[PDB]
Image (cartoon, rainbow over all chains, first blue to last red; front, side, top):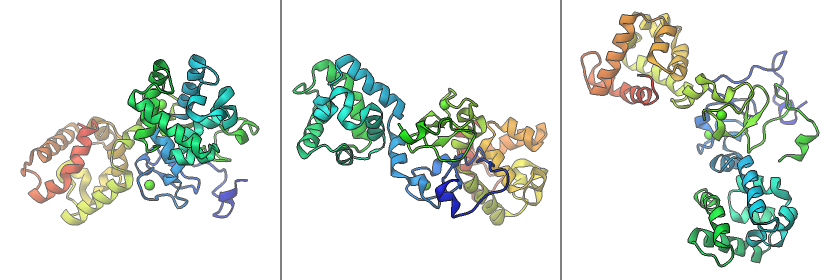
Length: 167
Length: 167
Ligand SMILES: [Ca+2]
Ligand SMILES: [Ca+2]
């Protein structure tokens, strides 16, 4: 009772022979691969899940539950509408127009670029451009948009976006 | 982070569906964790599979299958008894007395130290000491046991063992 799997076959009886410790990663296609083969620029799993772009981008960024916590702590320190200063009015009321802090944490973890993030979140041209200008300004030490404490709390996170190809 | 996943409840031990892209690694206990939480010194699976010592050793060493192809290439180039020069007489006839090339390649990948490898392969004290002397000689450029060409073929592999705690 699993979609993909119906059409390749059906194992033994019972199900489980999980992966060995030396090839500990199970692909949906049901091959076992070494951690080294994940995100290595070539497909080791027949379904190519080992090179899944969402999985490989998330592997480069903070774990989603740390980003969730981090978004929540900025709004607790700076206000429930604080993230309007970065993403525009869809960020008001604890990211209510962007699908909530859980959906935003996953999107910032998995989405390779600001452009693909903007499109998922339905930001217009002006909101996307302002998001990039604020994030460049946070890296600069600029306080045109954020206060000094706001920029310092955000700086390390924006640095990691930039080191991982977001902008 | 997944609205689908709330309303099926508890991810059993195991299968049915796969772990999401942001927490792609499945513990046998049925938890899903980020790659970054593997081998990080604290348990994120309730069964501590993320800190499993064999898994974590193997993740620092060449993949199983490369080590296996490597040992087979050494014995095709240098003879079916070539690895007697490292492991002693149990290595004769393509590692017959050590359970064969697949078992030796798994043991070299996932055994933390030369002493634990020796005890599992049932090498005696004399054989263990000579193995360590030969491996040191390979790092040195000594040709007392291997030719220049044999040692050149083995040197990177011996360095990967030294760098990952083997001796
Ligand atoms: Ca790969
Ligand atoms: Ca861990």
